Amino acid sequence: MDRKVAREFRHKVDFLIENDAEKDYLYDVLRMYHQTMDVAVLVGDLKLVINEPSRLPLFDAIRPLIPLKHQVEYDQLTPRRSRKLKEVRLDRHPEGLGLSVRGGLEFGCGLFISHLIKGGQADSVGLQVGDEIVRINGYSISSCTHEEVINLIRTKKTVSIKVRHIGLIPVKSSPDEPLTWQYVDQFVS
Amino acid sequence: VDATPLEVFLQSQHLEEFLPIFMREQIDLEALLLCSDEDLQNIHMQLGPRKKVLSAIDKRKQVLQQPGQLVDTSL
Ligand SMILES: [Cl-]
Image 1: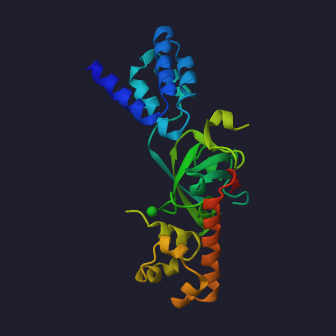
Image 2 (image 1 turned 45 degrees about the vertical axis):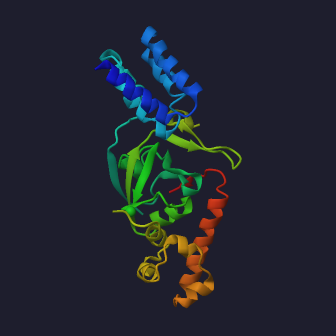
Image 3 (image 1 turned 90 degrees about the horizontal axis):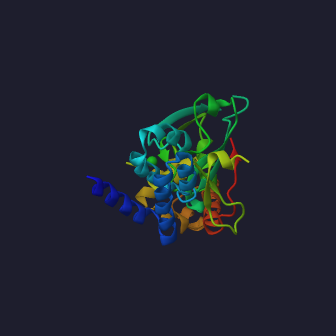
């Protein structure tokens, strides 16, 4: 039943990574770790290839091969890969919602919490930097431009927010640049 | 099942009251962006919401063509 694992992983790699050089890198990465058994280096190496939200499921595919002795440090080092959806209701508080938000349809990427004011209302309720805001007021926002979403958030007295924790932030720092992604701990600066 | 892109669109703009007329005229969001001020006068939209609709349509047409940089909106 080992060949079943290898096959499954090899095609999920083929499907989620276009360039052969990054594939070769990925396999070399895990192979090096399989010799070193250094898990901090493995996640540190993995993040330079699993760089975009579509590739994040490879952290779960790699995961069953991780020895239990490394399992928990693996979890400390990976973004939270739980697919569960946290739902929230925020009220119009003198300091406001207490979050900052970036992305939208015109960028071809979802809408992410990029800043969370410590102690504000968003933090009171457990939202976190790196959540993708999936829904607002019950509506999927996938067809909304950025300004449309901000409009939709401001339509009523309170705002319903359902997020899925991603752990990546979109970065394009002016129009020339292609959109890429960064992990949360780095993006803060 | 989800709201159509037209519905979310109008919802975001406080224009939700026009979803039943746009549907009777078979106006999806595709067709909506093809509409002029005079098109919307033909279905008896009054001046106030005409301006709000066309403002929203034009903001959307522009950022789809020129997204610009990613921006942080503080809420
Ligand atoms: Cl919806």
